[PDB]
Amino acid sequence: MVEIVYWSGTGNTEAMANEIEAAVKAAGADVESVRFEDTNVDDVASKDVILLGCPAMGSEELEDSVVEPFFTDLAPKLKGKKVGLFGSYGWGSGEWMDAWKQRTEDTGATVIGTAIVNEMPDNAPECKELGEAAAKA
Ligand SMILES: Cc1cc2c(cc1C)N(C[C@H](O)[C@H](O)[C@H](O)COP(=O)(O)O)c1[nH]c(=O)[nH]c(=O)c1N2
Image (cartoon, rainbow, N blue to C red; front, side, top):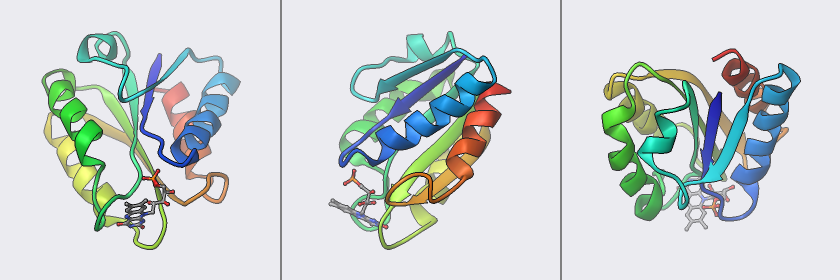
């Protein structure tokens, strides 16, 4: 059981989440895909595996006004659980995802892969890989 929580500006992370979802469904696993704006730590608690979807913003950062408020709320129950990280970038890779990995790992949770894409999904099999991994917790 996987809660795929995504923040999508320009369709990108939605389509990424959809790709992941298909790989989860292929291995007969229950998926709950929602947006960062409409979720809660209590919901997350019921799912052994969680995936977070945030594109690269400003100067190689996470999306401050939604993802960081939800992350702080999430932190008390982000222990032991399998958390996969998925994001789209334009011109700069890695940094935002490294900082993101560091904070998600740091709460006592483990990272069930990191998917980085050049704007649009499919261009990185990583998305599908994360799907498979999430299906298998
Ligand atoms: C205000 C703003 C700021 C950034 C971006 C876009 C926008 C609109 N993008 C590109 C972005 O990661 C890419 O286009 C995503 O596929 C879509 O991101 P959003 O859904 O538009 O936030 C971007 N890309 C990148 O590689 N490093 C960066 O720091 C940023 N910063």
